[PDB]
Image (cartoon, helix red, strand yellow):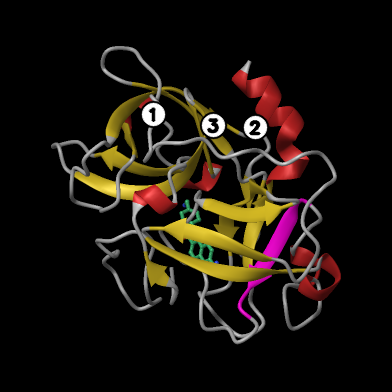
Amino acid sequence: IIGGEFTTIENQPWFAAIYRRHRGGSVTYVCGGSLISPCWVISATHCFIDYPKKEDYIVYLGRSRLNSNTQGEMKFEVENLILHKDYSADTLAHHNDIALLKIRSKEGRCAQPSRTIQTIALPSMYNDPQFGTSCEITGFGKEQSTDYLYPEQLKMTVVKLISHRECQQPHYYGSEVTTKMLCAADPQWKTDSCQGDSGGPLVCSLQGRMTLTGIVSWGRGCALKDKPGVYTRVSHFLPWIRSHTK
Ligand SMILES: N=C(N)c1ccc2cc(C(=O)Nc3ccc(CN)cc3)ccc2c1
């Protein structure tokens, strides 16, 4: 997250921290995710497509720092890694950038909701917020495009949704951004999601309900003028999510 503020997991309890175990035992941070039900985390296929072995992943719920075993956190392995069959990547645009991780503890259990571990509601069909609405993003991603380390403490920020007509302007993304994608950015271009925030949530308060409107997917650079963050429009994928979690 470029700009924004530092936060803790009690303010983002649906946030899942996803790591990968390498041959030799080293563990590194991969992407964010969101808890949609006790056994299921939703994220972005681009985070996993190059290393599609479910046994390699470690998922934490209730974790506030990259390298601290936060009090109340829960550690899981991935029982099922479901990638969207029509996923693809263009130079900038990522298509069908959505994945599901069925989680299980070493005892064979799913998440136990608590003050620091909670689900996030899915949106309803054809009902996304209007352009100009403020939404929040969360993640352990880069603080500056030039950084190589990620921040130790979880971050969040707030951005505004941008219309499809505006996002398709020539100086924005033209025809590369589709109706299955949602743009969001800062009008002053000072805060945005960045590398390492992929798969994490774009949460919008809509009609009084905190909703998982988007999943961090792609963008040209980070916090660049006329280059919004681009998010998978979760409402389009409700049939796919329902069918793959039954
Ligand atoms: N401007 C944004 N909001 C934004 C939003 C998301 C971003 C994602 C990546 C990134 O590194 N993506 C990526 C894509 C595919 C693969 C798999 N090879 C790995 C990483 C890099 C920069 C990003 C910037």
How dense is the environment of label 3, judged by Cα within 10 Å: few (below 14), some, or many (20 and up)?
many
Q: Quarter-wise, where is residue 56 in the image?
A: top left
Percent x, y for residue 174?
79, 72
- Left or right relative to 70: residue 230: right
Region rendered in magenta: 180-186
Label annotation for residue 169: none
What's the residue type where badge 1 is placed? Answer: Lys
Check if residue 68 falls in the magenta segment. no
Percent x, y for residue 19?
31, 42
Q: Earlier in the sequence, mark 1 or mark 3?
A: 1
Instruction: Name the residue: 30% across, 51% down.
Output: 64
What's the residue type where badge 2 is placed? Answer: Lys
| Labelled pair 2, 1 in contact (Cβ < 8 Å) | no
Position above or below: 213 against 120: below
Percent x, y for residue 215?
59, 50
Position above or below: 162 against 81: below
The residue under label 2 is 85
Instruction: Name the residue: 36% across, 42% down.
Output: 18
Distance in Å between CA atoms under marks 2 and 1 = 16 Å
What's the residue type where badge 3 is placed? Answer: Leu
The residue under label 1 is 53
Distance in Å between CA atoms under marks 1 and 3 = 13 Å
- Left or right relative to 124: residue 85: left
Instruction: Name the residue: 38% across, 38% down.
Output: 115
* Disc number lying in front (2 or 3): 3
Viewer-side residue, 94 vs 40: 40
The residue under label 3 is 100
Quick one: quadrant of the N terminus?
A: bottom left
Quick one: quadrant of the C terminus?
A: top right
